[PDB]
Structure formats: C-alpha cells, structure tokens
Image (cartoon, rainbow, N blue to C red; front, side):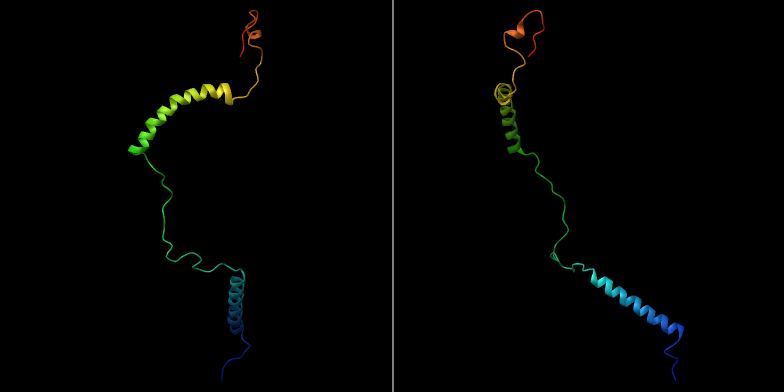
Length: 103
C-alpha cells in the first residue's frame, strides 16, 4: 500500500516538475533562431590581407614618380585655377611703398 498523494516531499517533486515546466515554456517563448541558419559546411576564415608590392606595381611607382613632377605643375595651376579665392588688394595697390606688400 503506497504513501499519500499528500506528503511534503511529493509536493516538492511536483514543485520541481512545475519549475522545469516554466523553464521549457519561457525558453521556448523567447524565439531564438535555430541551428543551421548559415551553411554547416561554413568553415573558419582569416581577415582581409590587401595586395603588396611587385615588379609591375613598382613600375607604376616609377610612373607615379613621373606623374609627381607633372603634379608639381598641376599644384601651381591648382592655385592658379582650382582655387577660386578672391584677392585681398589690387596688383599695383599692394606695392605702394609706405606699407608692406601682402598677397
């Protein structure tokens, strides 16, 4: 003949089954996306590692050194034509001798 549907430890083992049932419920209700959202064959990788110098990118560099002496030209004309800043004072007025000439 069994013990009662009525002991304190029987109620505590039902209380444990209830705490687990609340866990299975919250843990389900929060809606995490499941495993295998990306490919399971999606291997580990490295970072980006962008090109280094070679012979051909060296010879573009010798032509960059060329395009640099014409960039010296394109800088002076940079001032003459890309810069559109108005004068402070007139080309002949700036040379009036009892004050400093100021471009």
